[PDB]
Image (cartoon, rainbow, N blue to C red; front, top):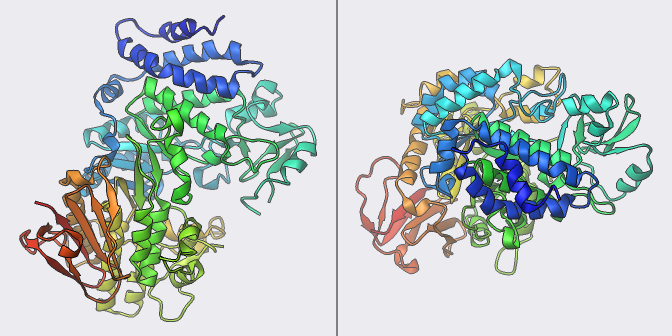
Length: 625
């Protein structure tokens, strides 16, 4: 048998230089049983399995051999769980909006380094469909930088610059579907049945019709598109020019694993795995969140474990926190799937708590946050390139006997300025999500409109408060580009025939480097925000209690306006989500004489306290000494 365990190790060994292959073959021996078990489960009976597996493993070995020395070094030196250390801070941005090009990004590395960023997410920058391309999410080549943004050489140079600054690049890997002008799609359109089989194709409406009875439409239109060139119905979950890959075909698994490693070899250190819920289709289901989708992620993780162990696997899935634990792996796979998942529940709860002046909403979220397996952590965030999806908080909004319900529509209408008096200037997305920048959402725009200096200062307090919550979490707190300067909404897109249909442009502004130049000027908005965030980031970096290995807990306080969380046994963070100054008796919760840290940037001590008086929207960080 060509696929004997021994012959499989041989397929990989056949590509490696015996002299630099010891480390790779050792990791193969460790992780291959898990990988091969998963591949067998997925593809064991596929007609091409036996002929596919050995040559694919050889191709994997070839890509492993090509792994640059500088990246091999990270593989060898990075400890498990490195991405959850307390000095980890993240930043998410579009390449064009941030600095135009990959070269431009490289030139702004010192800005990121000074901010304290160790984890940089650049939104989709790989070559994407000609014309409409779903904001870069319709990918035409997983192995080539979008030319208007730069070349592969520029990416190599950028990641080398990033590594010197101790920064890790995170890139999107759109696993579920490709642009219809991807090379595989073009080969299908040219009649090559091998590549046609890289996608889901049907000669007539018979199966699509039946699938339509159980599928949920994402863009209410359709899940299938007739392609005249091939005269087939193609599965198109999202836009008609995005064809769903056929993950039941092992060739597709092989190709995508290789594309991942080839990105890693250009210096990508973390993969935002997108649209993973849709990877597996099963007749008679909604074709979402099938067990096989996780098995695929397990297999990809094992490939990374063998070839590029310093790489991080991140689930993109924006869902209620209760639905996230499967991404960290189930059963013997626990700790062997995704390293990271997004804490969207906490994000939405922050905004809700702020609008309703109810810290108890956050208390509840922390109290029920899923425990993190070893080498797993959260991405915590306040905003992102998408609208705020309130739906993740549906469960909490229903409330309980001990927790009063709240209205998600009331929160959304607040932020869309749909009720008189509101300080927010967001907009409803075409319960509907909310578009807008953090600064416009917390009251900065409205304060300016009213020429109100006091109201602007309260807005800043709210912004810093939301970020403080993220910064105390186990994992990577992720700053959305420009929030560190309180960048405002961008309305110019309304005048752009090509962009006006897309409301999310409101919160996708270009970086204003003239405001960035003001970040140390305490007398400016940019400077006040940046300095206050830096104070927290600096403290975070010096607190081992905040590392992802340490516990996360909540402390119930008598007042629903307050919110308290603990990290490990030596850190406590107390928050006031109201506009009223409120006292806290530390002895009530066994925190008497804990020291108050200098979160504001001068008190100045720190000193032991037995009680606190928290200003409106206030944050206090305390350490056990």
